[PDB]
Amino acid sequence: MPAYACQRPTPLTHHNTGLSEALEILAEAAGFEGSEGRLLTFCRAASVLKALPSPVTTLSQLQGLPHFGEHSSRVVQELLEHGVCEEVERVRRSERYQTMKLFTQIFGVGVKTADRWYREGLRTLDDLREQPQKLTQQQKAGLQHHQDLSTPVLRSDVDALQQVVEEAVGQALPGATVTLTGGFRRGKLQGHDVDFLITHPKEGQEAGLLPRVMCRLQDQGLILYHQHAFERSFCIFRLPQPGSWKAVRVDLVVAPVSQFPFALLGWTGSKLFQRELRRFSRKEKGLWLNSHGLFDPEQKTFFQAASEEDIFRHLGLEYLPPEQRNA
DNA sequence: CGGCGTACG
DNA sequence: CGTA
DNA sequence: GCCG
Ligand SMILES: Nc1ccn([C@@H]2O[C@H](COP(=O)(O)CP(=O)(O)OP(=O)(O)O)[C@@H](O)[C@H]2O)c(=O)n1
Ligand SMILES: [Cl-]
Ligand SMILES: [Cl-]
Ligand SMILES: [Cl-]
Ligand SMILES: [Mg+2]
Ligand SMILES: [Mg+2]
Ligand code: NA
Ligand code: NA
């Protein structure tokens, strides 16, 4: 088992679901306390279990696995012996965990904001609604739409959404394309949002595209919220439902076609897969990776990739299709 | 011990 | 600060 | 919390 998530296939469904879920609770709790290192270790340990070919049944099967030390191994031991880990259950029922989870789940609210509200004594969404002077426009939209945004987006919703985005994109710039990325490209059947990557085959033609797209979607009455020169939009969309509609989060990102492989790789995720890939690139290969390119800081050159396959090859990694990037 | 991804709005 |  |  290699130490980086980008070195191993991770399928969407696997054989250690309960164990990985418990470790991810501790990871999330570590994040709520600002402990990014512990969050990373617990996330990595969870991801290792996702990559295993069969269920862990005995503690000895953790021997030699990366990112399993005394703490993660004890969590697993207790789950194997008793079906429950007391530390995990204590986190789950704690007021701190439940409130930080509730608040950071709001669109427009991060750990720092949630923590400040928590220290001020706030605990419920209605607590926030009662004091709306403390809210940004983004947070107001996130709170108003919170119920709908808490409902999973279905893969069966995505196609109709992509069609309306394609229509607006085609008027904004004929020949521009829309590619589904994020979790649905990794095979997820549900998601928290839909992520789309937009480009044009003629380098440079995509400049100034996203304002034109957003203006057209807004004119069609489809935009319940957006932040408005820009290249990423985090918006709330009106999606039809039988006899009504629901609010859905949609992300739109424009890249020049020269950068499209990097943007596709970046936006397809998973989040942990991309952090691990960038860490691998820099620490093992001495190359700096982001959603724009892959930089050699010794030659001061950028790698001109034509595909995701190109990028994996340049990093000395076996290619992983999106469905195996579910770290 | 230091390090822990890297951007844009 | 928020977002991916 | 764990790796190197
Ligand atoms: N911090 C971040 C946040 C995001 N990303 C990248 O953005 C993609 C979509 O994020 P996303 O937030 O839409 C999560 P997704 O994987 O699509 O699942 P969901 O929407 O059903 O929850 C991720 O899969 C990563 O490639 C990242 O690199 N670093
Ligand atoms: Cl930490
Ligand atoms: Cl590609
Ligand atoms: Cl980036
Ligand atoms: Mg998504
Ligand atoms: Mg997204
Ligand atoms: Na949030
Ligand atoms: Na960095």
Image (cartoon, coloured by chain):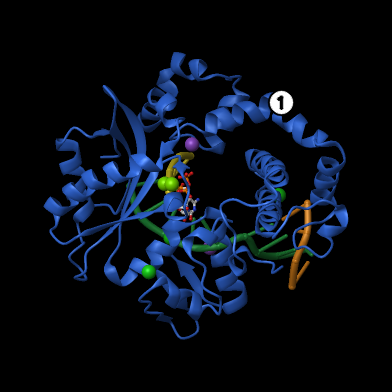
Chain colours: A blue, B green, C yellow, D orange
Whole-percent x, y for residue A266 in the image: 44, 61
Whole-percent x, y for residue A115 in the image: 59, 32
Which corner quadrant holds the N terminus of chain A? Answer: bottom right
Q: Is residue A271 left or right of residue A303?
A: right
Quick check: which quadrant has ligand 3? bottom left
- Residue at 38 percent across and 45 percent down: it is A194
- Residue at 45 percent across and 30 percent down: it is A151
Q: Is residue A111 left or right of residue A301?
A: right
Q: Observer-nearest residue: A222 or A239?
A: A239
Residue at the extreme bottom of the image, as rendered: A299
Whole-percent x, y for residue A125 in the image: 50, 20
Task: Specify the quadrant of the image occupied by residue A92.
Answer: top right
Whole-percent x, y for residue A129 in the image: 44, 17
Residue at the extreme front of the image, as rendered: A54
- Residue at 20 percent across and 61 percent down: it is A207
Identify residue type, mark 1: Arg
Q: Is residue A135 visible?
A: no
List the residue tagged with mark 1: A93
